[PDB]
Amino acid sequence: QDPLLAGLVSLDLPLDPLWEFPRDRLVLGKPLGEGCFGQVVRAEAFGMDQASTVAVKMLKDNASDKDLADLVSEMEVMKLIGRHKNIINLLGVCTQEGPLYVILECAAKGNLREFLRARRPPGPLSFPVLVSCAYQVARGMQYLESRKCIHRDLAARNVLVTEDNVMKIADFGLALPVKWMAPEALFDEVYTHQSDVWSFGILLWEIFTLGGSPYPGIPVEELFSLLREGHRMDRPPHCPPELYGLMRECWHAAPSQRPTFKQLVEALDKVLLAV
Ligand SMILES: *CCC(=O)Nc1ccc(CN2C(=O)N(c3cc(OC)cc(OC)c3)Cc3cnc(Nc4ccc(N5CCN(C)CC5)cc4)nc32)cc1
């Protein structure tokens, strides 16, 4: 569906030597995630002669030309963003023989919401652990921001956790969200780094409720009035007033009066020090 994937015996994509990875240094494995976002499998990559575990995205066997365009586009965007510890990094691509493969870092523990929820108490998710989670995501957003990247969908479901409990921001939209959207984004479809800061506030609340759902009991069509009327979430039980103070600053109606990601990193770093 239709002309490029049906008509071509081979897809003559341009060779980019900086990123091309040999297909025979790759051992494809088990599917990864629930497949909302294309086909992604776990794999072993050799010499990234030590293996290492990676994630590999490819086209579903019924993909359309539009899915082809989206994967290439995602791939091209990730080449320009550059690497950072707290984001899902591009590791390589396979474009020259056979199937298009996009190789990404694997985060073995899944997404941050589920990680938190699984380790809820009846400890594991101590204050220092939660602050560390927040801090790492803020560092990743600070980086993304410095590359002029606006996420637009920052949420704990979109932060992946590696084997070493490193936070890695994923992004499935490089090519439901309403409870994470800044008022300017809801009402006027305006997206800025400051609207990401608002989302980060919602993520902070997610962290300190141990994977709780935002605005419990409130239907998405009402968030509408509520946010305009100045409604904000309350303090999570597992949360010092000072961290709640940060959340609340992130939900300022005025984008200029929300902290910057640089500020959030410095404040969270200081809390971490105090342990
Ligand atoms: C609808 C819910 C859903 O399916 N979510 C989901 C889909 C796919 C993946 C797999 N990915 C992934 O998409 N990553 C990624 C790809 C990409 O393409 C351009 C860009 C990204 O950011 C810019 C990221 C890469 C990646 C890295 N690590 C993991 N790790 C992971 C481990 C375990 C699990 N689970 C295992 C078992 N169970 C029961 C639940 C979850 C999921 C992911 N995945 C991906 C992830 C989520």
Image: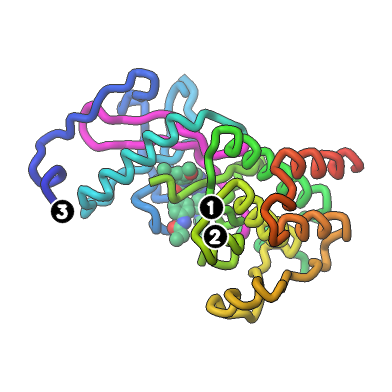
Q: Do the residues labelled 2 and 1 touch (CB within 8 Å)?
A: yes
Q: Can residue 119 be seen in this view?
A: no
- Rate crowding at label 3 as few (under 14), some (14 to 19) or many (20 or more) other CA atoms within 10 Å: few
User: Which of the pair 131/163 is nearer the observer?
Assistant: 131
Q: Mark 1 points at which residue?
A: 191
Q: Is residue 103 magenta?
A: yes
Q: Mark 2 points at which residue?
A: 185
User: Which of the pair 157/42 is nearer the observer?
Assistant: 157
164 to 245, vertically: above or below: above
Q: Does the residue labelled 3 lie within 8 Å of ligand 1?
A: no
Magenta stretch bounds: 86-113
- Rate crowding at label 1 as few (under 14), some (14 to 19) or many (20 or more) other CA atoms within 10 Å: some
Going from N to C along the chain, the mark reached first, 2 or 1, is 2
Mark drawn on residue 13? none
Q: What element carries label 1?
A: loop
The amino acid pointed to by label 3 is: Gln
Q: Are marks 2 and 3 in contact (CB under 8 Å)?
A: no
Please indicate whether residue 262 sits to the left or right of residue 42 in the image.
right
Mark drawn on residue 1? 3
- How far across and how far down the image is residue 145, in percent? 60, 38
Farthest residue toward the right?
A: 274
Q: Real-space Cα distance between discs 1 and 3?
A: 32 Å
Going from N to C along the chain, the mark reached first, 1 or 3, is 3
Please indicate whether residue 70 sits to the left or right of residue 217 in the image.
left
The amino acid pointed to by label 1 is: Tyr
Q: Is mark 3 on a helix, strand or loop?
A: loop
Residue occupying the point 58% across, 79% down: 222
